[PDB]
Image 1 (spheres, rainbow, N blue to C red):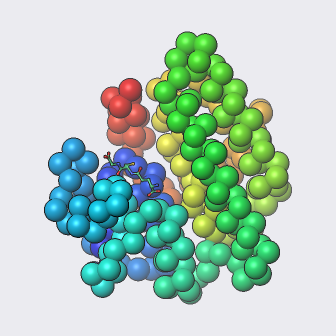
Image 2: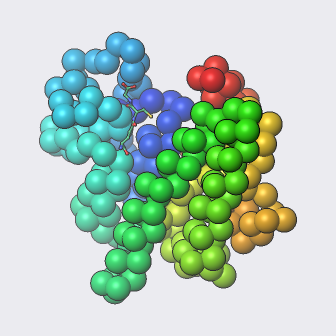
Image 3: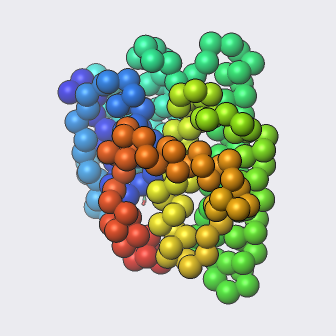
Length: 212
Ligand SMILES: N[C@@H](CCC(=O)N[C@@H](CS)C(=O)NCC(=O)O)C(=O)O
């Protein structure tokens, strides 16, 4: 109500927006899209990309999850998900942009097989070690003592990557090699705002498996 969210159930890109809206207490109408039979509404609201998610606020559409998250932060500023200091805001945006590199590494791992899969697993691990060492550090959350937009952007490193790891038979994010990032991902997975708003583990696995 007031806000509509066009999504796809198994997509972390959609889950990101749900978490942000719940952290802001904003009520929304969720519309599930069939990506092989896209609604007329989705095609009208996101003509450029024809992708979910799309947030519609008072009949005006915002596409692209990272753009939507910034819009939510600016439109409902209470309970900030970005810091005030411009430098710390720039560091948040920097690590969100590093998410592009992370998604690419996740994608190569997702698609890898044989000695390719072992390559991509090693490269994903190296990508995550940089994120852990230079991004997260010794903080409980990327946002410090509470989640910020960076935590939301990387939350898929828990439930989603875990499902992919199971399907692939290879675990990359593990406590022995990434103790701080693994603890972060586990803690985020156990947070009610996340745990209540991701698919059941069995459904998530079933999905990634199929996709493969
Ligand atoms: N950069 C976009 C990516 C979103 C995206 O890739 N959405 C996929 C589903 S996870 C999609 O809608 N694909 C349309 C299609 O399958 O043709 C974002 O962050 O919102």
